[PDB]
Image (cartoon, rainbow, N blue to C red; front, side, top):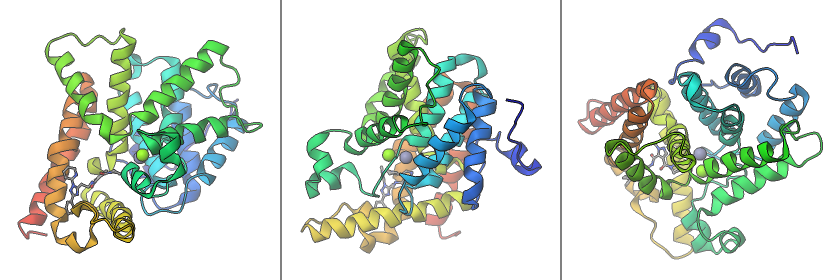
Amino acid sequence: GLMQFTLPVRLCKEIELFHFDIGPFENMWPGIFVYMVHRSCGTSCFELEKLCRFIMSVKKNYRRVPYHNWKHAVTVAHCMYAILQNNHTLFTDLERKGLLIACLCHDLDHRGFSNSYLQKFDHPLAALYSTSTMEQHHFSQTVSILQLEGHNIFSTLSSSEYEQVLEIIRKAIIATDLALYFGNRKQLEEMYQTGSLNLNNQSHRDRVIGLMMTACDLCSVTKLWPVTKLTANDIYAEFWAEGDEMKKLGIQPIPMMDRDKKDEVPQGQLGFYNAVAIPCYTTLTQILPPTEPLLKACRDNLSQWEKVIRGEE
Ligand SMILES: Cn1ncc(C(=O)N2CCC2)c1C(=O)NCCc1nc(-c2ccccc2)nn1-c1ccccn1
Ligand SMILES: [Mg+2]
Ligand SMILES: [Zn+2]
Protein backbone atom coordinates (compact mmCIF):
# COMPACT_ATOMS: atom_id res chain seq x y z
CA GLY A 1 0.00 0.00 0.00
CA LEU A 2 2.86 2.42 0.99
CA MET A 3 4.94 0.98 -2.00
CA GLN A 4 5.37 3.61 -4.78
CA PHE A 5 7.11 2.91 -8.08
CA THR A 6 9.63 5.77 -8.72
CA LEU A 7 11.68 6.29 -11.87
CA PRO A 8 15.11 7.82 -12.36
CA VAL A 9 14.95 11.63 -12.56
CA ARG A 10 15.19 11.97 -16.40
CA LEU A 11 12.31 9.42 -16.77
CA CYS A 12 10.33 10.87 -13.82
CA LYS A 13 10.26 14.26 -15.70
CA GLU A 14 10.12 13.19 -19.36
CA ILE A 15 7.36 10.48 -18.84
CA GLU A 16 4.89 13.43 -18.33
CA LEU A 17 5.54 14.82 -21.85
CA PHE A 18 3.61 13.52 -24.92
CA HIS A 19 6.91 12.92 -26.90
CA PHE A 20 8.45 10.59 -24.23
CA ASP A 21 10.07 7.38 -25.68
CA ILE A 22 9.97 4.34 -23.30
CA GLY A 23 13.55 3.42 -24.30
CA PRO A 24 15.23 0.14 -25.31
CA PHE A 25 15.26 -1.58 -21.87
CA GLU A 26 12.34 -4.06 -22.11
CA ASN A 27 12.65 -4.95 -18.36
CA MET A 28 11.75 -1.33 -17.38
CA TRP A 29 8.46 -1.22 -19.44
CA PRO A 30 6.31 -3.03 -16.77
CA GLY A 31 7.48 -0.63 -14.01
CA ILE A 32 6.86 2.33 -16.34
CA PHE A 33 3.25 1.14 -16.98
CA VAL A 34 2.57 0.59 -13.22
CA TYR A 35 4.02 4.08 -12.48
CA MET A 36 1.49 5.48 -14.99
CA VAL A 37 -1.46 3.49 -13.57
CA HIS A 38 -0.50 4.70 -10.02
CA ARG A 39 -0.29 8.45 -10.96
CA SER A 40 -3.21 8.31 -13.50
CA CYS A 41 -5.67 6.17 -11.51
CA GLY A 42 -4.24 5.73 -7.96
CA THR A 43 -2.17 3.15 -5.97
CA SER A 44 -5.57 1.56 -4.92
CA CYS A 45 -7.03 1.08 -8.50
CA PHE A 46 -5.51 -2.45 -8.78
CA GLU A 47 -4.08 -5.11 -6.41
CA LEU A 48 -0.33 -4.81 -7.23
CA GLU A 49 0.06 -8.65 -7.21
CA LYS A 50 -2.81 -9.11 -9.78
CA LEU A 51 -1.69 -6.12 -11.88
CA CYS A 52 1.92 -7.41 -12.18
CA ARG A 53 0.59 -10.90 -13.14
CA PHE A 54 -1.86 -9.37 -15.69
CA ILE A 55 0.99 -7.18 -17.24
CA MET A 56 3.35 -10.22 -17.60
CA SER A 57 0.57 -12.39 -19.18
CA VAL A 58 -0.21 -9.47 -21.60
CA LYS A 59 3.53 -9.20 -22.51
CA LYS A 60 3.66 -12.99 -23.12
CA ASN A 61 0.67 -12.80 -25.59
CA TYR A 62 2.41 -10.12 -27.77
CA ARG A 63 4.59 -11.63 -30.55
CA ARG A 64 8.13 -10.88 -31.77
CA VAL A 65 7.01 -8.82 -34.79
CA PRO A 66 8.86 -5.65 -35.96
CA TYR A 67 6.10 -3.13 -35.00
CA HIS A 68 2.87 -4.64 -33.47
CA ASN A 69 4.82 -5.79 -30.38
CA TRP A 70 4.95 -5.24 -26.60
CA LYS A 71 6.96 -1.94 -27.01
CA HIS A 72 4.06 -0.65 -29.22
CA ALA A 73 1.52 -1.61 -26.51
CA VAL A 74 3.40 0.29 -23.77
CA THR A 75 4.08 3.29 -26.09
CA VAL A 76 0.31 3.56 -26.90
CA ALA A 77 -0.53 3.33 -23.15
CA HIS A 78 2.04 6.09 -22.40
CA CYS A 79 0.39 8.48 -24.94
CA MET A 80 -3.00 7.75 -23.25
CA TYR A 81 -1.35 8.49 -19.85
CA ALA A 82 -0.16 11.91 -21.11
CA ILE A 83 -3.70 12.68 -22.43
CA LEU A 84 -5.41 11.56 -19.15
CA GLN A 85 -2.90 13.54 -16.97
CA ASN A 86 -3.39 16.73 -19.08
CA ASN A 87 -7.28 16.42 -18.82
CA HIS A 88 -7.48 15.49 -15.08
CA THR A 89 -11.17 16.33 -14.51
CA LEU A 90 -12.80 15.26 -17.88
CA PHE A 91 -12.74 11.47 -17.18
CA THR A 92 -14.50 9.06 -14.76
CA ASP A 93 -12.69 6.69 -12.32
CA LEU A 94 -13.68 3.70 -14.56
CA GLU A 95 -12.48 5.44 -17.79
CA ARG A 96 -9.02 6.06 -16.20
CA LYS A 97 -8.81 2.33 -15.09
CA GLY A 98 -10.17 0.96 -18.40
CA LEU A 99 -8.29 3.08 -21.02
CA LEU A 100 -4.67 2.38 -19.87
CA ILE A 101 -5.57 -1.34 -19.79
CA ALA A 102 -7.29 -1.04 -23.23
CA CYS A 103 -4.13 0.55 -24.68
CA LEU A 104 -1.79 -2.09 -23.21
CA CYS A 105 -4.11 -4.82 -24.63
CA HIS A 106 -5.22 -3.17 -27.93
CA ASP A 107 -2.95 -5.28 -30.25
CA LEU A 108 -2.81 -8.58 -28.23
CA ASP A 109 -1.55 -11.56 -30.32
CA HIS A 110 -1.05 -9.42 -33.45
CA ARG A 111 0.74 -11.35 -36.24
CA GLY A 112 1.94 -8.25 -38.24
CA PHE A 113 -0.81 -8.69 -40.88
CA SER A 114 -3.76 -6.37 -41.69
CA ASN A 115 -7.48 -7.32 -41.68
CA SER A 116 -7.34 -7.46 -45.57
CA TYR A 117 -4.54 -10.09 -45.54
CA LEU A 118 -6.52 -12.30 -43.04
CA GLN A 119 -9.54 -12.00 -45.44
CA LYS A 120 -7.53 -12.82 -48.60
CA PHE A 121 -5.71 -15.70 -46.83
CA ASP A 122 -9.14 -16.94 -45.55
CA HIS A 123 -7.76 -17.11 -41.98
CA PRO A 124 -10.16 -18.74 -39.47
CA LEU A 125 -10.37 -15.36 -37.58
CA ALA A 126 -11.89 -13.75 -40.76
CA ALA A 127 -14.86 -16.23 -40.58
CA LEU A 128 -15.29 -15.67 -36.79
CA TYR A 129 -15.13 -11.79 -37.20
CA SER A 130 -16.13 -10.34 -40.64
CA THR A 131 -15.18 -6.68 -39.78
CA SER A 132 -12.44 -5.27 -37.49
CA THR A 133 -11.10 -8.88 -37.60
CA MET A 134 -7.87 -8.40 -35.52
CA GLU A 135 -9.50 -5.84 -33.15
CA GLN A 136 -12.28 -8.26 -32.14
CA HIS A 137 -9.50 -10.85 -31.61
CA HIS A 138 -7.47 -8.40 -29.41
CA PHE A 139 -10.56 -7.80 -27.17
CA SER A 140 -11.16 -11.62 -27.03
CA GLN A 141 -7.52 -12.12 -25.88
CA THR A 142 -8.04 -9.35 -23.24
CA VAL A 143 -11.13 -11.17 -21.78
CA SER A 144 -9.12 -14.50 -21.86
CA ILE A 145 -6.31 -13.02 -19.78
CA LEU A 146 -8.69 -11.22 -17.30
CA GLN A 147 -10.22 -14.71 -16.66
CA LEU A 148 -6.91 -16.50 -15.85
CA GLU A 149 -6.75 -17.27 -12.09
CA GLY A 150 -5.23 -14.37 -10.06
CA HIS A 151 -5.51 -12.06 -13.16
CA ASN A 152 -8.81 -10.29 -12.40
CA ILE A 153 -7.50 -6.75 -11.83
CA PHE A 154 -11.15 -5.52 -11.73
CA SER A 155 -12.24 -8.02 -8.98
CA THR A 156 -13.26 -5.18 -6.55
CA LEU A 157 -15.62 -3.51 -9.13
CA SER A 158 -19.42 -4.14 -8.78
CA SER A 159 -21.10 -6.42 -11.35
CA SER A 160 -22.36 -3.33 -13.35
CA GLU A 161 -19.08 -1.33 -12.89
CA TYR A 162 -17.22 -4.45 -14.22
CA GLU A 163 -19.58 -4.60 -17.28
CA GLN A 164 -19.14 -0.82 -17.94
CA VAL A 165 -15.26 -1.12 -17.83
CA LEU A 166 -15.20 -4.20 -20.21
CA GLU A 167 -17.53 -2.15 -22.46
CA ILE A 168 -15.12 0.87 -22.39
CA ILE A 169 -12.20 -1.51 -23.24
CA ARG A 170 -14.17 -3.22 -26.08
CA LYS A 171 -15.18 0.07 -27.82
CA ALA A 172 -11.64 1.54 -27.16
CA ILE A 173 -10.01 -1.54 -28.82
CA ILE A 174 -12.51 -1.72 -31.77
CA ALA A 175 -11.86 2.02 -32.44
CA THR A 176 -8.11 1.24 -33.18
CA ASP A 177 -9.41 -0.25 -36.48
CA LEU A 178 -8.24 2.66 -38.72
CA ALA A 179 -11.07 1.82 -41.25
CA LEU A 180 -13.47 3.16 -38.54
CA TYR A 181 -11.39 6.30 -37.76
CA PHE A 182 -12.46 8.39 -40.87
CA GLY A 183 -16.23 8.30 -40.21
CA ASN A 184 -15.62 8.71 -36.46
CA ARG A 185 -13.55 11.92 -36.90
CA LYS A 186 -16.02 13.36 -39.55
CA GLN A 187 -18.87 12.97 -37.01
CA LEU A 188 -16.77 14.52 -34.22
CA GLU A 189 -15.77 17.35 -36.65
CA GLU A 190 -19.49 18.15 -37.39
CA MET A 191 -20.63 17.85 -33.71
CA TYR A 192 -17.78 20.20 -32.56
CA GLN A 193 -18.51 22.82 -35.35
CA THR A 194 -22.37 22.76 -35.11
CA GLY A 195 -21.90 22.96 -31.28
CA SER A 196 -23.91 19.70 -30.71
CA LEU A 197 -20.90 17.94 -28.99
CA ASN A 198 -22.01 16.92 -25.42
CA LEU A 199 -19.65 14.94 -23.08
CA ASN A 200 -22.67 13.86 -20.87
CA ASN A 201 -23.96 12.08 -24.00
CA GLN A 202 -22.46 8.54 -23.61
CA SER A 203 -22.44 7.97 -27.45
CA HIS A 204 -20.46 11.28 -27.72
CA ARG A 205 -17.95 10.15 -25.05
CA ASP A 206 -17.58 6.86 -26.95
CA ARG A 207 -16.55 8.78 -30.14
CA VAL A 208 -14.11 11.05 -28.19
CA ILE A 209 -12.52 7.94 -26.51
CA GLY A 210 -12.29 6.38 -30.01
CA LEU A 211 -10.42 9.43 -31.37
CA MET A 212 -8.04 9.37 -28.33
CA MET A 213 -7.36 5.63 -29.21
CA THR A 214 -6.53 6.56 -32.84
CA ALA A 215 -4.32 9.41 -31.47
CA CYS A 216 -2.43 7.09 -29.02
CA ASP A 217 -2.20 4.27 -31.62
CA LEU A 218 -0.55 6.63 -34.22
CA CYS A 219 1.69 8.43 -31.58
CA SER A 220 4.98 7.45 -33.37
CA VAL A 221 4.28 10.53 -35.63
CA THR A 222 4.29 12.79 -32.45
CA LYS A 223 7.82 11.72 -31.30
CA LEU A 224 11.23 13.32 -31.92
CA TRP A 225 12.19 12.91 -35.58
CA PRO A 226 14.78 10.10 -34.99
CA VAL A 227 12.10 8.04 -33.05
CA THR A 228 9.49 8.75 -35.78
CA LYS A 229 11.87 7.82 -38.60
CA LEU A 230 13.14 4.54 -36.95
CA THR A 231 9.58 3.50 -35.97
CA ALA A 232 8.48 3.95 -39.66
CA ASN A 233 11.21 1.39 -40.59
CA ASP A 234 9.50 -1.18 -38.27
CA ILE A 235 6.07 -0.30 -39.72
CA TYR A 236 7.20 -0.91 -43.34
CA ALA A 237 9.13 -4.10 -42.29
CA GLU A 238 5.70 -5.56 -41.39
CA PHE A 239 3.91 -4.06 -44.44
CA TRP A 240 6.53 -5.43 -46.89
CA ALA A 241 6.38 -8.95 -45.30
CA GLU A 242 2.55 -8.69 -45.83
CA GLY A 243 3.26 -7.59 -49.44
CA ASP A 244 5.49 -10.65 -50.00
CA GLU A 245 2.65 -12.84 -48.59
CA MET A 246 0.09 -11.16 -50.98
CA LYS A 247 2.45 -12.00 -53.92
CA LYS A 248 2.54 -15.66 -52.67
CA LEU A 249 -1.33 -15.75 -52.85
CA GLY A 250 -0.96 -14.43 -56.49
CA ILE A 251 -2.10 -10.80 -55.69
CA GLN A 252 -0.11 -7.60 -56.47
CA PRO A 253 -0.06 -5.87 -53.05
CA ILE A 254 -0.95 -2.14 -52.77
CA PRO A 255 2.26 -0.02 -53.26
CA MET A 256 2.41 0.78 -49.45
CA MET A 257 3.16 -2.96 -48.95
CA ASP A 258 5.37 -3.50 -52.02
CA ARG A 259 9.10 -3.41 -51.02
CA ASP A 260 9.82 -2.80 -54.77
CA LYS A 261 8.25 0.70 -54.25
CA LYS A 262 10.47 1.72 -51.19
CA ASP A 263 11.43 4.93 -53.12
CA GLU A 264 7.79 6.21 -52.70
CA VAL A 265 7.74 6.03 -48.83
CA PRO A 266 8.37 9.78 -48.23
CA GLN A 267 5.39 10.75 -50.49
CA GLY A 268 3.28 8.01 -48.75
CA GLN A 269 4.18 9.59 -45.37
CA LEU A 270 2.86 13.03 -46.61
CA GLY A 271 -0.42 11.31 -47.73
CA PHE A 272 -0.59 9.66 -44.26
CA TYR A 273 0.13 12.90 -42.27
CA ASN A 274 -2.35 14.93 -44.47
CA ALA A 275 -5.12 12.25 -44.77
CA VAL A 276 -4.87 10.63 -41.25
CA ALA A 277 -2.45 11.97 -38.62
CA ILE A 278 -2.92 15.82 -38.87
CA PRO A 279 -6.74 15.67 -39.07
CA CYS A 280 -6.73 13.23 -36.09
CA TYR A 281 -4.67 15.49 -33.76
CA THR A 282 -6.46 18.69 -35.06
CA THR A 283 -9.96 17.39 -34.07
CA LEU A 284 -8.45 15.98 -30.85
CA THR A 285 -6.97 19.44 -29.98
CA GLN A 286 -10.37 21.12 -30.76
CA ILE A 287 -12.11 18.73 -28.30
CA LEU A 288 -9.24 18.58 -25.70
CA PRO A 289 -7.11 21.73 -25.91
CA PRO A 290 -4.21 20.49 -23.69
CA THR A 291 -3.44 17.70 -26.32
CA GLU A 292 -2.04 20.45 -28.63
CA PRO A 293 1.61 19.28 -28.28
CA LEU A 294 0.60 16.08 -30.24
CA LEU A 295 -0.67 18.26 -33.16
CA LYS A 296 2.44 20.49 -32.97
CA ALA A 297 4.84 17.44 -32.87
CA CYS A 298 2.93 15.83 -35.83
CA ARG A 299 3.28 19.04 -37.90
CA ASP A 300 7.06 19.11 -37.13
CA ASN A 301 7.38 15.46 -38.37
CA LEU A 302 5.35 16.30 -41.54
CA SER A 303 7.89 19.08 -42.23
CA GLN A 304 10.77 16.54 -41.67
CA TRP A 305 9.23 14.17 -44.33
CA GLU A 306 8.90 17.23 -46.64
CA LYS A 307 12.67 17.84 -46.12
CA VAL A 308 13.32 14.16 -46.93
CA ILE A 309 11.51 14.57 -50.33
CA ARG A 310 13.47 17.83 -51.10
CA GLY A 311 16.73 15.79 -50.68
CA GLU A 312 17.65 17.93 -47.56
CA GLU A 313 17.83 14.42 -45.84
C1 LIG B 1 3.34 6.13 -39.43
N1 LIG B 1 2.21 5.23 -39.27
N2 LIG B 1 1.60 4.91 -38.08
C2 LIG B 1 0.66 3.97 -38.33
C3 LIG B 1 0.71 3.70 -39.67
C4 LIG B 1 -0.24 2.65 -40.25
O1 LIG B 1 -0.77 2.85 -41.28
N3 LIG B 1 -0.70 1.58 -39.53
C5 LIG B 1 -1.69 0.53 -39.78
C6 LIG B 1 -0.84 -0.32 -38.93
C7 LIG B 1 -0.29 0.91 -38.31
C8 LIG B 1 1.68 4.50 -40.28
C9 LIG B 1 2.17 4.53 -41.68
O2 LIG B 1 3.26 4.91 -41.97
N4 LIG B 1 1.36 4.10 -42.74
C10 LIG B 1 1.88 4.08 -44.10
C11 LIG B 1 1.44 5.39 -44.77
C12 LIG B 1 1.56 5.25 -46.24
N5 LIG B 1 2.65 4.77 -46.88
C13 LIG B 1 2.32 4.80 -48.19
C14 LIG B 1 3.16 4.36 -49.30
C15 LIG B 1 2.64 4.31 -50.58
C16 LIG B 1 3.51 3.88 -51.59
C17 LIG B 1 4.82 3.50 -51.33
C18 LIG B 1 5.29 3.55 -50.04
C19 LIG B 1 4.45 3.98 -49.01
N6 LIG B 1 1.13 5.34 -48.37
N7 LIG B 1 0.63 5.62 -47.15
C20 LIG B 1 -0.64 6.23 -46.94
C21 LIG B 1 -0.99 7.32 -47.77
C22 LIG B 1 -2.21 7.92 -47.61
C23 LIG B 1 -3.08 7.49 -46.65
C24 LIG B 1 -2.76 6.39 -45.82
N8 LIG B 1 -1.53 5.75 -45.99
MG1 LIG C 1 -4.22 -2.71 -34.11
ZN1 LIG D 1 -1.76 -0.49 -32.37
